Image (cartoon, rainbow, N blue to C red; front, side, top):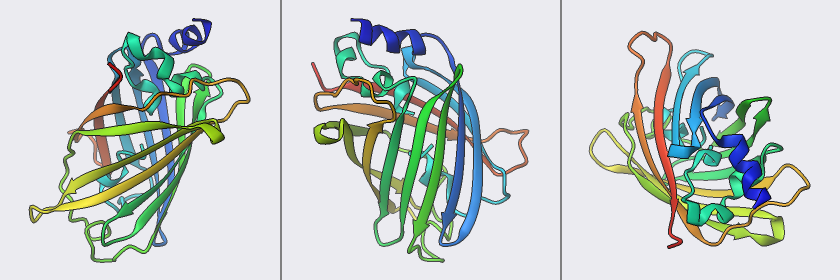
Length: 230
C-alpha cells in the first residue's frame, strides 16, 4: 500500500528527536529542551529533557504526556490505522486540555513534524488555576510513572482523531492525583491521512536521572504499542 510505504520509509530505523517547550503555569514561566531518538519498529523512545530556565516550577511527571505518538509500534495487522505516521512529513497538531482533579489545568498546543531528518515536537503550555500549595505547584508528586492505555477514535468531521484518558500520578503521602486528559490531533498538510478504527496505545514510561547532570532534568524511556484490533 503506497500510503503505508511513505510512513514506513520515514520511520524505519532510529530517528533523532528534538522537543521544545515554552510554559507558563500561574505566571511561573519556564522553558524545556529535549533530545533523544525513537525507533518506531520497537515502539521505543529515549529522551532527556532539561529545564533551561532553572528550576522547573511543576513536577516533571506532570509533563510526560505533553513531551510523540508517531513512534508507536503498530502491529502489521493494524498499519492501516496509524494516523500519526500517515500525516508525516508535514506533521500534525496535538492539542490538549489536562484537568488536575481539585487543582488547575494545562492547555497545550504542539506541532509534530519533520525538520529534515529530525522529528520535532514544538509545544506551548499554559496552566491556570493552580493552588500555590497544591500537589503540582507544591511539588508533592513522586518521581515515577504508571502504565496506561490511551483510546484513540476518529474525529471524522475534523479529518483527525480524538483521544481521551486518565493518568494517576502518585502523591508522596501515598494517595493519587488524577489528571484527566482531553486530546485532539489534526494534520498540518492538505493531503490524505489514515483515519483509524477505535483502538488504543499501551504506554509504559520509566523516569530516571542523569548522574552527571546538574541542571533540573528528566530522562524518559517509553515503549508504546498499538492494540485492540484483533
